[PDB]
């Protein structure tokens, strides 16, 4: 399958999440996503077909993971945006106040600004530190999905947020949103991965 | 292109405002370390802020008396606490939680010169108890109600 940021993938035929970014570990293909999306060895499927398995993950504490894919998968330096896409050009972290957008299978492509860094979230499973907060809206299913700037600089992967009964926080003003993401560089660094760029 | 629509729709950034915003985003990135170096121990954070007229600007806070910066394009804001002070309170909160029903999250927020503790609507008391047990200086922390749940 075509590995693109923001697309839906299932875990163990039980849960859903969104692809973060295409990456490589030497000759090994893969994609980064949220740690809460799957446990080590969990099977990832796209379009019903097995594409890889969770190679490593950390959650809580952090909220990161990467899926090692089969050589048959096609890695692309993109993030879905409607019928088009955003080209991934690098991973330079943007400042607080910078405009950023995220992509996911539920709310699609949504934009806002980075509002805070090094946030500790009190998730039910346990605290996760070091998250970045933005005010673009999101919803259940967008987890693990891409967060990127307008100029194509990959920022991180969706970790969680203050969603409402409807499953998202798009129904409340951006000023009241808490949409959190795990920074990309620490994931790449911990697992020795390289971001696929174009 | 398709990003412009999203930017205008979600951020209220119209095409003609794009260049100036981009210039500010880049400035915030390229000067971040230089600003921190200049403000020294009194550094209190920096961020991109949007003006009422739609333009953007780079702001840098300091707990010192400094009223200007050597680097251009930087608005200096005088605040009470330094980043180091806020960071210490933040660490106390982390420690307190490491040993919290109602508490959503917490983080150093330079723009408001305080550590923010977000709580579910109607859980301010939980936020109060959390801050107290953490031993964090209440003057450096501010509780903010947050809709929905994490
Ligand atoms: S995922 O990271 O997008 C995300 C979205 C919504 C939830 C439910 C929060 N109560 C969790 C994670």
Image: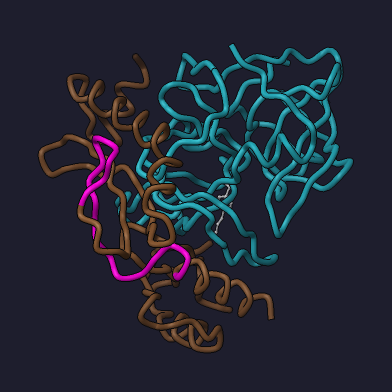
Chain colours: A cyan, B brown
Quadrant placement of the N terminus of chain A:
top right
Residue at (41%, 68%) from the top-left corner? B116
Query: Which residue is outermost to the left?
Result: B53
Nearer to us in this view, B43 or B53: B43
Depicted B95 relative to depicted A125: above or below: below
Residue at (61%, 80%) from the top-left corner? B96
Q: Is residue B17 left or right of residue B97?
A: left
Picture quadrant where residue B120 is located: bottom left
Q: Is residue A73 left or right of residue B139?
A: right
The image shows residue A51 at horizontal and vertical percentages of: 81, 24
The image shows residue B97 at horizontal and vertical percentages of: 62, 76
Nearer to us in this view, B38 or B130: B38
The image shows residue A135 at horizontal and vertical percentages of: 39, 47
Depicted A78 relative to depicted B145: above or below: above
Depicted A56 relative to depicted B134: above or below: above
Residue at (37%, 35%) from the top-left corner? A99
Depicted B1 relative to depicted A25: above or below: above
Residue at (42%, 34%) from the top-left corner? B29
- In magenta, the rendered stretch is B68-85
Query: Which residue is outermost to the right?
Result: A41
Quadrant placement of the C terminus of chain A:
top right
The image shows residue A69 at horizontal and vertical percentages of: 82, 24
Q: Is residue A197 left or right of residue B24?
A: right
State yes or no: residue B81 in magenta.
yes
State yes or no: residue A23 in magenta.
no
């Amino acid at each position: 399958a075509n590995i693109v940021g923001g697309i839906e993938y299932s875990i163990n035929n039980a849960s859903l999440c969104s692809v973060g970014f295409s990456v490589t570990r030497g000759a090994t293909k893969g994609f980064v996503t949220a740690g809460h999306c799957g446990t080590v060895n969990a099977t990832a499927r796209i379009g019903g077909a097995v594409v890889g398995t969770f190679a490593a993950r950390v959650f809580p504490g952090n909220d990161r993971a990467w899926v090692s894919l089969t050589s048959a998968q096609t890695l692309l330096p993109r993030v879905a945006n409607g019928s088009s896409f955003v080209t991934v050009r690098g991973s330079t972290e943007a400042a607080v106040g910078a405009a950023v957008c995220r992509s996911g299978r539920t709310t699609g492509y949504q934009c806002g600004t980075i509002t805070a860094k090094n946030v500790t979230a009190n998730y039910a499973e346990g605290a996760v530190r070091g998250l970045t907060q933005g005010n673009a809206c999101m919803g259940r299913g967008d987890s693990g999905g891409s967060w990127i700037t307008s100029a194509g600089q990959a920022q991180g992967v969706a970790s969680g947020g203050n969603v409402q009964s409807n499953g998202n926080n798009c129904g409340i003003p951006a000023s009241q949103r808490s949409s959190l993401f795990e920074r990309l560089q620490p994931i790449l660094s911990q697992y020795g991965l390289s971001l696929v760029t174009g | 292109p398709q990003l412009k629509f999203a930017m205008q729709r979600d951020l209220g950034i119209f095409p003609t405002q794009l260049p100036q915003y981009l210039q500010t985003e880049k400035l915030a990135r390229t000067q971040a370390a230089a600003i921190e170096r200049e403000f020294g121990a009194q550094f209190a954070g920096s961020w991109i802020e949007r003006n009422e007229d739609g333009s953007f600007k780079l702001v840098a806070a300091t707990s010192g008396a400094r009223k200007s910066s050597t680097l251009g394009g930087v608005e200096v804001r005088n605040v009470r606490y330094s980043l180091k002070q806020l960071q210490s309170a933040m660490e106390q909160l982390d420690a307190g939680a490491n040993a919290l029903d109602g508490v959503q999250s917490w983080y150093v927020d330079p723009r408001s010169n305080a550590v923010v503790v977000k709580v579910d609507d109607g859980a301010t008391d939980a936020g109060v108890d959390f801050v107290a047990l953490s031993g964090a200086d209440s003057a450096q922390v501010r509780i903010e109600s947050s809709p929905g749940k994490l």
